[PDB]
Length: 182
Image (cartoon, rainbow, N blue to C red; front, side, top):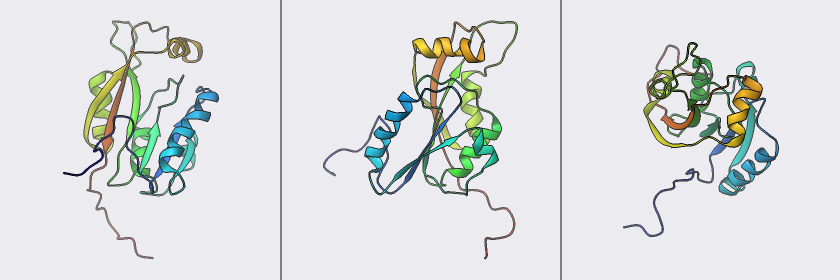
């Protein structure tokens, strides 16, 4: 029976690992200024918080297993859709024995034109992209900003919406061809 505490419903990061925060052309600047201070306290000096761009991540792909926990779509006042190319890229940067954190919205309103995926597909997207043990953790209502942002920038005019955070772990099966030998 270890003393202290075992668990964390806030994040779960230790000193030594590298944390990243991807943002899109929409998220404010103030919220981002404090979002780093929160993670900086967890990493301290051993760890480091590196902020990258979702649009640049494709043009400038990072090495494999370079990061441990990369936050994707977790910035206040930010509504962007993720594709297989993005979810697949984030999985490559993440380590084989780490954790992933993503938060994408879900639509369930009867309309003539569909754009946003469903809750089920949102979870399966990570399971098919290249993750294991993918399951919904929790969900939180929308904010006065996110509700208008979806209509301001994107312009969908969606009234019925809901945010759902789903985590995804990295498996251990990528034995292709040609071992790394320099």
